[PDB]
Amino acid sequence: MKFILAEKFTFDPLSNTLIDKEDSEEIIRLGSNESRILWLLAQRPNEVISRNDLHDFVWREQGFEVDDSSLTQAISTLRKMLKDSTKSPQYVKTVPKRGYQLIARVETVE
Amino acid sequence: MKFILAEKFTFDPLSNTLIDKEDSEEIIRLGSNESRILWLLAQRPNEVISRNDLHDFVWREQGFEVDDSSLTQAISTLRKMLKDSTKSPQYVKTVPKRGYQLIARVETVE
Amino acid sequence: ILLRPVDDLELTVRSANCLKAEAIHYIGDLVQRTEVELLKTPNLGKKSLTEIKDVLASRGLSLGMRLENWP
């Protein structure tokens, strides 16, 4: 099933592609880790998810263990490639001591 | 058991032949390894397969003993024969440390 | 020596994470697995293997040796 974020981007959890409607010619390529993190965010629309829980769901299914700086770097690359605001709450933000938040709307294509 | 891939190719593993919808007369010859690779990708359309699984299923059936990088060479040859850009994959994706992916549409006639 | 936590080995955090990937808990577990078995691992590559084997040689017990009735 394909998801639409903030009526602007479209993304699918199964093929890991991003499409911007403003520039439909340029497909945006994302890494597997950030794509799975964003999909997990989309599964829970706009409610807080713990850093610990999202981290362990993303990487323990991968079969291997990494430090928690990897999560921060993945979110940094997610915000950078999406051209989301550096620290304003436009699409994705970080809520301290509680976890991570998404602001973009969820539109299931099918 | 013949497949259609991405609404463009017709794949025959029993005859290891690849046919284009654009080029119906042109039938391209693929080696045994590439045919088995694509056959497993088709048997699991879009679920992520593992490198150990491919090396096993391909070369444990014939009893061949090859190194792991032979899988990489087989995938490279398949990519060059499918005219699939590695930078922007449309048929075969490399999911790092998990294996490969068949993102193209796969249909089973009979 | 074979009964100490792999923590007491002074290895790079990458190596420790990789060893937790295979659930290596204590030392001696690390020594009954050869180099080819270990290298077939996500993220446990060449330089990490050289570091782990050099620290093992500082312990003096390189990878491979077998013992009796463990544990």
Image (cartoon, coloured by chain):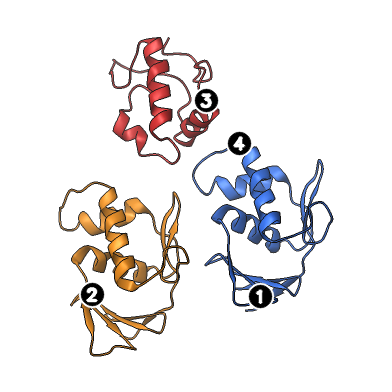
Chain colours: A blue, B orange, C red
Q: Where is mark 2, residue-wise?
A: B13
Q: Which residue is mark 3?
A: C12
4 and 3 marks in contact (CB < 8 Å):
no
Secondary structure found at label 4: loop
Label 2, label 1: how far apart the Cα atoms are: 39 Å
**Which chain is home to disc 4?**
A
Element carrying mark 2: loop
Amino acid carrying label 4: it is: Asp
Up-down: is A104 above or below A52?
below
Q: Are marks 2 and 1 in contact (CB under 8 Å)?
A: no
x then y, percent, for residue B59: 21, 55
C35 on left or right of A6: left
The answer to which quarter of the image holds residue C44 is top left
Q: Say which amino acid is labelled 3.
A: Thr
**Mark 1 highlights which residue?**
A23
| A104 or C34: nearer the viewer | A104
Residue tagged 4: A67
Residue at the spot 39% in from the left edge and 68% down from the top edge: B44
